[PDB]
Structures are given as C-alpha cells and as structure tokens.
Amino acid sequence: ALADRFAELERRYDARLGVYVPATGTTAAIEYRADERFAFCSTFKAPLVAAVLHQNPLTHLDKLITYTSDDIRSISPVAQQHVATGMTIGQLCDAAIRYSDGTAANLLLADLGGPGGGTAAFTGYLRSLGDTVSRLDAEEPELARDPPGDERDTTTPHAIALVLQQLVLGNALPPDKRALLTDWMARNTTGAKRIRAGFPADWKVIDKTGTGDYGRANDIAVVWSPTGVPYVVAVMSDRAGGGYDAEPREALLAEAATCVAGVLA
Ligand SMILES: CCn1ccn(C(=O)N[C@@H](C(=O)N[C@@H](Cc2cccc(C(=O)O)c2)B(O)O)c2ccc(O)cc2)c(=O)c1=O
C-alpha cells in the first residue's frame, strides 16, 4: 500500500521522506515517518507571518522597516532590491512567503522581539497553538544547515500539519488576518514542482516550501478538491546519505504528493 510506495520513493531518491495528512470527517490520516524530526528550513516562514499578524493590528503592516546591505545574510530575492527604500512589514510578509525571502524572515523575527532575535518568541507562538514539538533556535541561513539528527530548528510532518491546519482552516487567526496568510500562500512562486506538481489542475493548492543542505526539500500545503473539500498536506525530505552538498530532489515531493492525491480523489 501507501507505506510500501513511500519506501520505494526513499530507495529511488536515496532519501528520507516524511508525510502527514490530517484525518477529516470522512478520511483517515495519511502518515509516513510523521513523528520523526525534520529541519523546518523555510517552511517556518508561513507560521512566522501568522505570529506577526496575530501580535499586531492591521496598521502594523504599513510600518516601514529600514535595513542595510550588510543585514542581507541569506537568499533574499525581494529584500536585495529595497535596501535604499526599506520595506513595510506587509511587504516583508509577502516576500517571506512568496519568495522565501530570508532577510524578510529575519526582520520579521526581530519584529517579534525577545531573546534569540525573535526565535524564542516564534517558538512560543507555536506553543500557543498546541505545538510542543517544534523548535526554532537560529535565524536565516543557519537554521537550514544543522546536521541530520540535530534537534535544533526541527519540526515533524505531524506537528507542522496541525499548525497549518489551525492557521488556514481553523480559527487561530481572525478572518481578515487569516485571509492575508491564505492569499500570500496562494500566490507563492516557489512551489510549482513540489506538492502542486502532484495534484491535478482542478485542485487548488496553496503552499510554503523549504530547502536546505543535506538535500533538504520540504513543502507544506492546504489543498481543495474539485468540489471544495480541504486537506492539509505536509511533505518533508532529506538526503543525508549524500552529505552536506546533497542535491534536494523536488521530484521526490511531487511523486509523494501524487500518491496522496490519488488516495484523496
Ligand atoms: C552567507 C551566504 N549564505 C550562505 C548560506 N546560505 C544558505 O544556506 N541558504 C539556505 C536558505 O536560505 N534556504 C531557504 C530557502 C531558499 C530561499 C530562496 C531561494 C532558494 C533557492 O534555492 O533558490 C532557497 B530556507 O531556509 O529553506 C539554502 C540552503 C540550501 C539550499 O540548497 C538553498 C538555500 C545563504 O542563504 C547565504 O546567503
């Protein structure tokens, strides 16, 4: 069944794969290594934006943040182009999710305040959603580079799925803020070859990707069936057998997602 197919994907890509799809009223949970730890990588940027939204009025989105070239210490497709002008908190949220912008993520972490440049506050926000598992210990780009087995900067497919479920389908955020998070994930630019590539075109997919060393490739998504039925899909992977320089394999995530989509259809 599904377990054997996931295991064959692991063999095919020389990878470790984790999958979680929460149960619904009519479907069973799908789980494969769902309670094993995997590095967040940039998937944390989605609940990070939720934390900032939660903690502030909507007018906070229009606050201008200034930063320097030396502040850019991670891949930052949007922030690279706005050193002179700055970026608003809302623009940083947009960039963090839609382009996986690392400087935007670090500035949003800083905006949360507190120890660890915001990382403790972020972890605290997850705790407020009942996630006692995940932890963020570093900012970008260090958080994507911990050795396999290190618990720093890790979550589990199970844990992050339940968090994303509350944020997008639940009531963790009031409707107006929830709609912002959902819109940013819906217009993500980095996910076409991952969960999106596993679901037929008549399914809606919103997502946030993560990529790291040791061949890390993650994607977390909410998907809607052609009749409007929602599901949460978390897929995480690494290729520790290839060492630090191992190439991430998007096709592994696309194949895993295709397996999931077939079961959910
Ligand atoms: C100081 C210079 N330096 C050094 C290392 N570094 C870094 O490791 N970045 C990982 C990363 O940002 N990851 C974010 C993802 C990201 C964001 C934007 C683009 C890309 C891309 O691959 O094109 C990837 B996240 O935390 O998941 C990363 C790790 C492995 C990769 O194959 C790609 C990027 C830097 O960004 C960096 O600026």
Image (cartoon, helix red, strand yellow):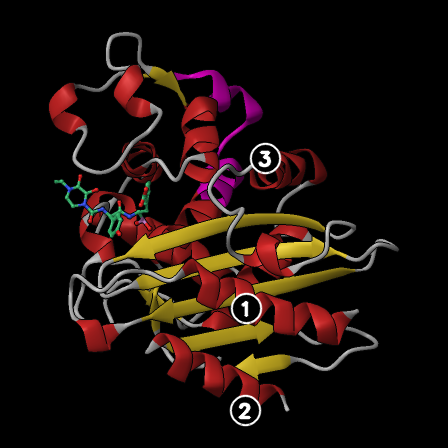
Tell me which segment is drawn in magenta. 49-64
Q: Residues within 10 Å of mark 2 (few under 14, many from 20)?
A: few
Q: Label 3, on which residue? A: 187
Residue 162 in sight = no
Q: Is residue 57 magenta?
A: yes
Q: Which residue is mark 2?
A: 4
Q: Earlier in the sequence, mark 1 or mark 3?
A: 3
Going 53% across and 62% down the picture, which residue do you hit? 254
Q: Which residue is mark 1?
A: 255
Q: Nearer the viewer, residue 52 or 219?
A: 219
Image quarter where the C terminus lies is bottom right
Q: Amino acid at mark 2?
A: Asp
Q: Is residue 99 above or below residue 115?
A: above
Q: Residues within 10 Å of mark 1 (few under 14, many from 20)?
A: some
Measured as percent of width and height from the top left, residue 194 is found at 51, 56
Q: Is residue 20 left or right of residue 46?
A: right
Instruction: For ligand 1, give the image quadrant.
Output: top left
On the image, the x and y values in percent for residue 2 come to 61, 86
Disc 1 + disc 3, Cβ < 8 Å: no
